Length: 47
Length: 47
Image (spheres, each protein chain N blue to C red):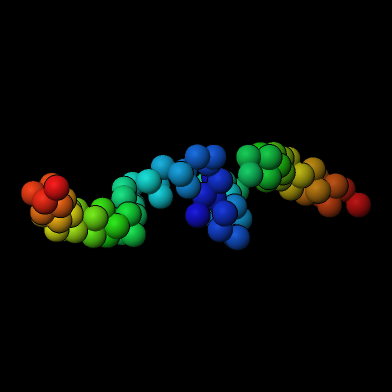
């Protein structure tokens, strides 16, 4: 509720520094990483 | 600097309850009143 240009951008950036969806995507990939490491180690161990 | 309807009216009314010009007009007429009273009393005293 204002007429000042640029207030919307600043206030939105302050309210939500990082969107929830991106945080959850990062969490999912990071949590799945160790299984990938184990799988590639197993593949390396053979041939 | 706002988008709220009616904020301009309220804020202007609070800033300037009475305009200067109207106060000065009232002052001029009120200050001139006693001379009018004296003149009309003089007119009445004759005829």
